[PDB]
Length: 207
Image 1 (tube, rainbow, N blue to C red):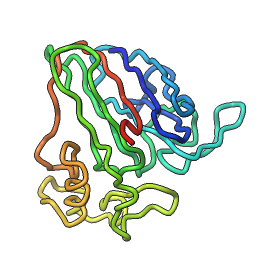
Image 2 (cartoon, rainbow, N blue to C red):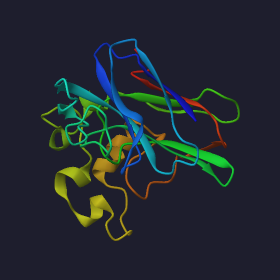
Image 3 (cartoon, helix red, strand yellow):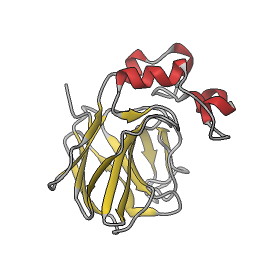
Image 4 (cartoon, rainbow, N blue to C red):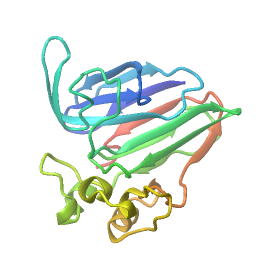
């Protein structure tokens, strides 16, 4: 797939793209407000994620820190980022189809739209002001709104046994963003797209 990653936020973000044990394309890059970065994701990538990082500082070797979404201090991510991170998630060329979603299961930092740029399916979006409205006990001082599993580390929030139900915290993310996963066993909001579609992830898609 080709992904165009566009920062429509008024602040700089450092986009990241990884499948957990490797970078996708270069794995990360700075996007000033307005900039677009086109990456090539290998067909058949299963469990890929793209997210924004904020308030980062990197040295000339690409090593440093971000306040949200830091991936082991690298500009170019090889692993997933530290919550809170709104996630654009995808698995491509899986028995002829691609599957996309947005998830708040690892919290939320930056609003996002994740849409195909080719035919055949619809996009998904979580662009509500989740950081402004975040329950006090989930607020991340470093910036963003943490998920309840990150904050409290219980079997019920982290759905460790695969049992779990919705919670007062998952329901906040679901009320602000119905079309994103709010906890691990949420009713799925995954969209099926034709195999080998292309996509655009836009940070701060609205006002």
